[PDB]
């Protein structure tokens, strides 16, 4: 439910 | 503090720190590697990004927890508990700002100016936009508009290069667009721009998938799904 | 560094740090609270325990990852990669030892000597055994037997008090027995003693459950299940 | 599969 940003 | 350690040993230890989930150490090792003054390879840029994103990610999550408690403390009917919630939120905020300033300082001295290939330049300018965006998340005072504009400007330069020099499926181009779209939605109060960017980015990548190997297809479609996740949440 | 902050504010901020999953900060706040020189309440003892167990738990997990890599590096057929794995394992080990020494120092100056009630004294002596046990996990040299015996001695004094002064279902008594049993299995090379202790502890608690309220029953049976989990793994 | 000690 939290928007995605570019991670990992 | 890393000046006496070999560059290769710093990189080796950053990879060990990642395996051990010791992200503060990982970031300190990668800062030391950057400060040797040589350009970073693709792998080394991704180690730098992983390390600092994990460090700041923990700080941001803690800041949001504390900010929510502070907000509830200033609602009507709340008992006065003293300055401690604000003080501790400020402590975490100052540490977060320090990490952002450290990353921005590495980018300015001297990673961006020596980055000539599109893959490296776009990567670093995206990073610059990201860390200004994290500063904007906690900003409240006279320079807040300037912090927001610094994020915007870095993202915009990265977008201009990425559109000219990279295919629409390139993972750095896609991750940049994802993050600039979040910037528009969450920071710049521009949800329509955020949605338009995510949709155009998704559609242009879809049309280029036919050119890719199986492995590149997997990489690109993973990030496209993140764009879709946001479009589903926002519409 | 916490000397200028009020005791109550340190405790308040430790609880905020827990909510934010900032366990290093939580531990620093609780160390400051201990150093005010007053005895700790039940709640405050549990905040101290939570904070340091989380800090050292992260260090121990990282140490095990690095120790495994180091072990594989010294197998026949492994390529020589230099001193970096050993150096980084040593760095994490030294930080872990420092945290254990800090906790043991708080217990010795002056928590244990002022603890007269069974609940507090057993809690602190269990903690002393625990942090000597963590030192034993990484020990390799001339004092290793003495480190192991220091853990044993602290656990044994806590057990003697707990058996005389607490019911067999008391959660501190149960958690002590759980950890002393792990000490026997993993540190002292005494798996039969570990199994016997876990079984007797479980059975004696079971026989006393009838005396408890619903809420106390829930607390005691949760720890009994941990004993059972180990018995199932070990038999 | 890792043995339990007293935590949380
Ligand atoms: C999968 N992935 C992360 C999710 S976007 C990337 O490829 C990537 C990592 C760092 C910067 C960037 F622009 C892209
Ligand atoms: C549930 N629980 C933790 C699992 S043993 C406790 O009650 C407890 C916490 C700290 C010390 C102790 F002896 C017992
Ligand atoms: Cl504070
Ligand atoms: Cl090291
Ligand atoms: Mg050199
Ligand atoms: Mg160059
Ligand atoms: Mg190109
Ligand atoms: Mg006072
Ligand atoms: Mg007393
Ligand atoms: Mg009693």
Image: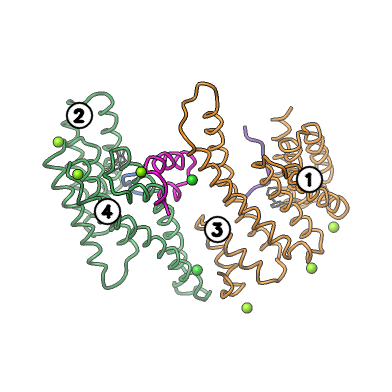
Chain colours: A blue, B green, C orange, D purple
Chain under callout 3: C
Q: CA distance from mark 1 to mark 4?
A: 52 Å
Q: CA distance from mark 1 to mark 2?
A: 65 Å
Residue C202 sits above or below residue C169 on the image: above
- Secondary structure category for the residue under label 1: helix
Q: Earlier in the sequence, mark 1 or mark 3?
A: 3
Reading the image, the residue beneath label 3 is: C18
Q: Residue B138's spot in the image, x, y percent?
A: 35, 64
Q: CA distance from mark 4 to mark 2?
A: 32 Å
| Residues marked 1 and 4, same chain | no
* Residue C37 in the figure: left or right of residue C208: left
Picture residue at 41% right of the left edge, 41% below the top: B9
Chain under callout 2: B
Reading the image, the residue beneath label 2 is: B209
| Residue D7 in magenta stretch | no
Chain under callout 1: C
Point out the frontmost of discs 1 and 2: 1
Q: Residues within 10 Å of mark 1 (few under 14, many from 20)?
A: some
Q: CA distance from mark 3 to mark 2?
A: 46 Å
Q: Residue B202's spot in the image, x, y percent?
A: 21, 39
- Secondary structure category for the residue under label 2: helix
Magenta highlight: main SS: helix
Q: Choose between B126 and C45: the one closer to the eye.
A: B126
Report the span colored magenta. B1-28
Q: CA distance from mark 4 to mark 3?
A: 34 Å
Residue B80 sits above or below residue C86 on the image: below
- Secondary structure category for the residue under label 4: helix
Q: Are marks 4 and 3 in contact (CB under 8 Å)?
A: no
Reading the image, the residue beneath label 4 is: B107
Reading the image, the residue beneath label 1 is: C149
Point out the frontmost of discs 1 and 3: 1
């Amino acid at each position: 439910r939290r928007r995605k940003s570019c991670q990992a | 503090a890393m000046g006496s350690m070999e560059r290769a040993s710093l990189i080796q230890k950053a990879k060990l720190a990642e395996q051990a989930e010791r992200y503060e150490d990982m970031a300190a090792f990668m800062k030391g590697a950057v400060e040797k003054g040589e350009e970073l390879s693709n792998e080394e840029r991704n180690l730098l990004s992983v390390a600092y994103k994990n460090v700041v990610g923990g700080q941001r999550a803690a800041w949001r927890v504390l900010s929510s408690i502070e907000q509830k403390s200033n609602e009507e009917g709340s008992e006065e508990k003293g300055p401690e919630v604000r003080e501790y939120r400020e402590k975490v905020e100052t540490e977060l700002q320090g990490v952002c300033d450290t990353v921005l300082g590495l980018l300015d001295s001297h990673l961006i100016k020596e980055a000539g290939d599109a893959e490296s330049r776009v990567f670093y300018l995206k990073m610059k936009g990201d860390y200004y965006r994290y500063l904007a998340e906690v900003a409240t005072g006279d320079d807040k508009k300037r912090i927001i504009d610094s994020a915007r400007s870095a993202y915009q330069e990265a977008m201009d290069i990425s559109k000219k020099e990279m295919p629409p499926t390139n993972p750095i181009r896609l991750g940049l667009a994802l993050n600039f779209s979040v910037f528009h939605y969450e920071i710049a109060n521009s949800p329509e721009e955020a949605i338009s960017l995510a949709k155009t980015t998704f559609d242009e990548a879809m049309a280029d998938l036919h050119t890719l190997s199986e492995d590149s297809y997997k990489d690109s479609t993973l990030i496209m799904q993140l764009l879709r996740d946001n479009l589903t949440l926002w519409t």
